[PDB]
Amino acid sequence: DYADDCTTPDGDQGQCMPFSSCRTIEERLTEAQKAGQKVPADYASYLQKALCGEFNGVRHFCCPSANIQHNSKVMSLFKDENFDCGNFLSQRVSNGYEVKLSSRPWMALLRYQQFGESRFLCGGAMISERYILTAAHCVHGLQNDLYEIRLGEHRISTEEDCRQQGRKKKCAPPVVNVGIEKHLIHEKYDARHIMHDIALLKLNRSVPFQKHIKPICLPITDELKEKAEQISTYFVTGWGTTENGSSSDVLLQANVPLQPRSACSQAYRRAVPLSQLCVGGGDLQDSCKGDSGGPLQAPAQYLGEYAPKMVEFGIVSQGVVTCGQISLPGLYTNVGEYVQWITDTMASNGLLES
Ligand SMILES: *[C@@H]1O[C@H](CO[C@@H]2O[C@@H](C)[C@@H](O)[C@@H](O)[C@@H]2O)[C@@H](O[C@@H]2O[C@H](CO)[C@@H](O[C@@H]3O[C@H](CO)[C@@H](O)[C@H](O)[C@@H]3O)[C@H](O)[C@H]2NC(C)=O)[C@H](O)[C@H]1NC(C)=O
Ligand SMILES: *[C@@H]1O[C@H](CO)[C@@H](O)[C@H](O)[C@H]1NC(C)=O
Ligand SMILES: [Ca+2]
Image (cartoon, rainbow, N blue to C red; front, side):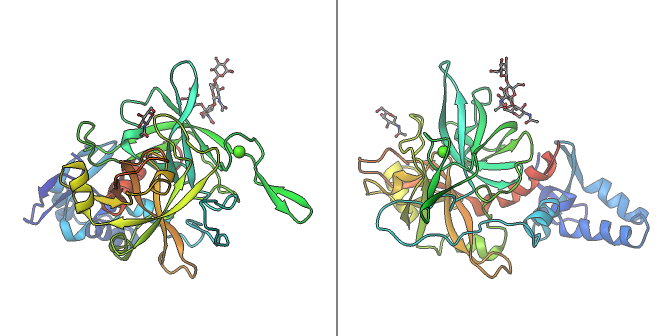
């Protein structure tokens, strides 16, 4: 299967990866192409021996562990100088939870058609013109119910979301309501224990970036993956969307602390692996601001960009409850541990049409 442990024909331990996620294979293939030639016969023979299957129409090869890289077919987008992810200024500091109109333009609302009606029951965040990142618990066993995504939202109840501009008002453009072509749940998602709680939703058309709809950045470098545990305070943003729908009509945000994993391991009476982050708890109105499957976000140095960019470091997995009651620390998916899976899943499923 994709990413299974394997041994290369030359005896190195590795994982079953697409060629675009193996620095050494990609270099050999690129070097031959650049010279206007095929790879030598002995190397073609090595690749046949290294072949570990075909998953979602992509040939996979055993790649030595140290040579595994994020999928170059997707990294070319994320590293593009014109890929405008995590852009924010954004607002002047108020004590409460208010969010400036359009200031978190990646925020997504997941719509479900159930008891004859439809409701937003999860959140998520735009990561590209065709992909939304969310929790697997928002998607698993719900493929027939989960049917639309809403992007560019601020206040759910009003079709027009405006702010004062002088003696007049400036409104954000209309929201975008888009369908879902693919429900892409992590292969190792455990629905019983809630582990590897991550999923991608591929939109059924491209949603071009607009002033109020833009992607969030991902922790695509070693520095950013390492940063997840060094950040003291994160933004927990959303409409407080749970199985009971949104608790807030308007987008809100709180500054919530990263906690030691022991806080969650004690509260949930279960081991907390490195693939999870422990956040917040012990408050009445802060930890609860997030959406089920929504982002855990913070500004960071993204590649060589001058301005800090917002990066999604976590995904709301468990323990984020309704406001007004004392919360327990919340479990979040540690996004850095899944960027490899994200890039390979987006690559095999296509950035544009499938
Ligand atoms: C992208 O997806 C949208 C939204 O549709 C949703 O996602 C799709 C991938 C499918 O899973 C849909 O079942 C799901 O609703 C598509 O727009 C929607 O198209 C459908 C079907 O042509 C419309 O349904 C009809 O609605 C009428 C009017 O009430 C009924 O009479 C019909 O019997 C049927 O239910 C639906 O109204 C429409 N929704 C929106 C918001 O436009 C869109 O076609 C699709 N493709 C592209 C290229 O965007
Ligand atoms: C959903 O509402 C019910 C009924 O009040 C409550 O028991 C529950 O905790 C809510 N779920 C979440 C995740 O907050
Ligand atoms: Ca609105």
